[PDB]
Amino acid sequence: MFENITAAPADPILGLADLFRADERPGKINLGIGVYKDETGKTPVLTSVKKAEQYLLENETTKNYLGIDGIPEFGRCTQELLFGKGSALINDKRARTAQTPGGTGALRVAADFLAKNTSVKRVWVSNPSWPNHKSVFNSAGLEVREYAYYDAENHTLDFDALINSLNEAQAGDVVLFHGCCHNPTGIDPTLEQWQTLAQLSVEKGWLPLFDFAYQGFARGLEEDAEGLRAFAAMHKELIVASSYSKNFGLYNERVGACTLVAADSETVDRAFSQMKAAIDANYSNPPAHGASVVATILSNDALRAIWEQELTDMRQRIQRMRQLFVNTLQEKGANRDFSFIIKQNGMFSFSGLTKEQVLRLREEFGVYAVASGRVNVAGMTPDNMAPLCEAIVAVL
Amino acid sequence: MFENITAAPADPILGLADLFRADERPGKINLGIGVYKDETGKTPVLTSVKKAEQYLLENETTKNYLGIDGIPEFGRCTQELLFGKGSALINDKRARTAQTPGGTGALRVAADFLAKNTSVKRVWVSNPSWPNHKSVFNSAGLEVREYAYYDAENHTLDFDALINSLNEAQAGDVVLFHGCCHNPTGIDPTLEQWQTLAQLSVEKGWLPLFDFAYQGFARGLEEDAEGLRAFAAMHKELIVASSYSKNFGLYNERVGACTLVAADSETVDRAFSQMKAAIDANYSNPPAHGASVVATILSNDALRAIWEQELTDMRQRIQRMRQLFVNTLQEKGANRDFSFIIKQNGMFSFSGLTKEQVLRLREEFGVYAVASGRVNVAGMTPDNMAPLCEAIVAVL
């Protein structure tokens, strides 16, 4: 029935870093770990986090249902975080926002709501893509269509190619644009480059969707939130599926947003009254906690000032691990240009470790990087650099 | 596109109690409010709640991603809450559990996972049904099929009728059984009565699903969790989609479970490895908070002992409002037998207020009960009884 003749074959969190406990090793680190990690390789409760949580405990008098759209401040600031300021999408009210359990959990929200109401059948992808994006897309119809993103060799973005096999298929066809920077590649489009495909998405029907997981990680937070803004006062209709789990260190309590910015007020009202609709049908109403905690910081003149900064270093640290990794090669290695990393936004970079390198790695080297030469510059440590940079130059 | 030729017509939280602020009234209460409310008609942060939350704040060192299945204790106790003890479904390991954002959010989980893997096309319903169950069901295929539940007149359960037009359609057809007691009706099957349809679901293919939102509200918690247990060491395959939001007063932080109890270990493993699968595709991984907080109480010998009891009175209070409502009529009213309530589990009862009674109610009476003669015995107060019981006997 249900019973047998069931497949199994699960999501590869596990392509790496699980049984890292493994065969009782002296192993350095786990690299290609998604989440962020310090010089002790710890995943902490910020401070901001906790200083806001103190608030709640004593201030919260009701764990009563939170609205279907979650909370409205969470939005108003989500909103001015995204693209806004005093800025008119906010004042046009061309923008209407949703409290979603994750950005992951605001990307399917995007699916099943756009399946119906909207004339969507396909989702144009990116390659390499964050592969939980092929999956959550056929979660309610649709199909993903993986265009040309990274062109290998000189480890960068192909615009020659992307602007070719993306360009392709039909007017009511959507894409989901990728923030500042990428997964698995750390690669991005420049505002020159992006601004340039904004007018080309204005001119081909298209109609965007964006995955905004990392603001102020390796570009800035605001200029890194402008590679969206390129589009924002350009389009008419679009959507942002955003997170707080990377920049707030709030992975577990589930928070993101589903901002549909339709062309009016009254439109943005109903294209969304149906966006309103979706929520109910699974998890009617969002969780409060991490959500509460994102609005609260922003609110306290002296709490976000401490968050923004607690964010700054989560970066300084990433940006650090790049320049370091590479010194450790020019300084150590002297082989190939290990170069290209530093100048790629995020914690992710697509190492050029063609596959069974990444394998004659997990042994008598007890080292982990997820198959695609995909590493976490986040779990790349000062104390962890040296050991690593030996086992790279050994594997070549 | 998305833009216009969008419908709107939203979920009627709103069939009542929103604009209750309304036309500047002296109005009593809002009755038919779902959530629970005290003698001050407040929706509180229990104590248990907060005493567990103190724990977390200081004890929690990571807001790092929670597993896709959420936490395992949450399950192990969910598990022994459900049906277990030292009891073998637990030790057969015929049962395998999921941390879900709600029971609402563990009922679609049930849908899209059973759509595929499993040979399901229809969901047999109940009438009156909790109407967020027609909706979240066509959320990924399927169709609901509303059998005979309540037969009106002498305001009870029809077994004559239910055992007739439920019985009907085909072997790979499922139902979702309704806990102890009901929504909107407060009506239940007895263990004699239920035990009697257990062997008749064993004999017709069928294969259950249960909605377990209210344990220990107007039957007991355990005997009220046995009207499941009737089935549990009966079936082979089934599922429970449970909540903590009513019994934990944790509406907002989102918690429930998705317990698939397949016939073995290795089966329960894969019919579920696909149950494992679903989670990812929307909200990969559950929120921690309220989830954390449910396991923690159970754990502390002296914290659940305080929760179980904080639960006891949330009931004493409901059970109170029944006997009272009715005194207030025999004592006040003297008309019809207002009787039937007290002896119906939960906070809900299906008042016999045929529709435009419930309407020549919301005026110069400023009173609210959601259309179907559907009231909250939870928002029925001592100070609120008298006023109410005047406007009933006035409307007849």
Image (cartoon, coloured by chain):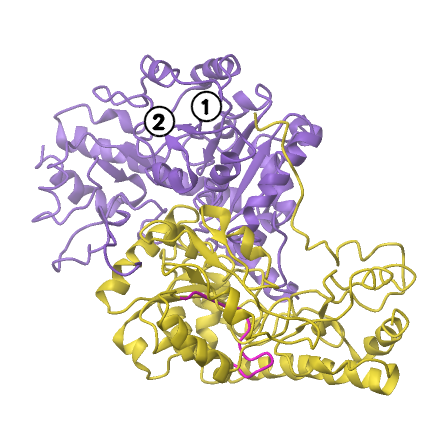
Chain colours: A yellow, B purple
> Left or right: where does residue A268 sit relative to residue A147?
left
Q: Residue at x 50, y 52 (%)?
A: B282
Work out whether residue A82 can be spotted.
no
* Amino acid type, callout 2: Arg
The disc numbered 2 marks a residue on which chain? B
**As rendered, which of B75 and A124 lies closer to the eye?**
A124
Vertical relation: B3 (above or below) B244: below
At label 1, the amino acid type is Asp
Q: Earlier in the sequence, mark 1 or mark 2?
A: 2
Q: Where is residue B239 drawn, in percent x and y?
A: 53, 32
Task: Please identify the dominant SS of the magenta region.
Answer: loop
Q: How far across and how far down the image is residue A55, in percent?
A: 48, 71
Have a look at marks 1 and 2 and say if they share a chain: yes
Q: Is A280 inside the magenta-drawn segment?
A: no
Instruction: Give the CA separation, mark 1 to mark 2.
Output: 10 Å
Q: How many marks?
A: 2
**SS of the residue at dot 2?**
loop
Q: Which residues are magenta?
A: A208-221
Q: Residue at x 43, y 51 (%)?
A: B251
Q: Which residue is mark 2?
A: B145
| B327, above or below A175, in the image | above
Q: Chain of mark 1?
A: B
Circle 1 Cα neighbour tier, 10 Å, few/some/many (<14 / 14–19 / ≥20): some
The answer to which quarter of the image holds residue B181 is top left
Q: Tell me if B165 is positioned left or right of A351 in this view.
A: left
Dots 1 and 2: beta carbons under 8 Å? yes
Residue B298 image point, x, y percent? 60, 45
Above or below for A201 versus B216: below
Is residue B49 or residue B101 the one in the foreground? B101
Q: Is residue A358 visible?
A: yes
Q: Quadrant of the C terminus of chain B?
A: top left
Q: Which residue is mark 1?
A: B173
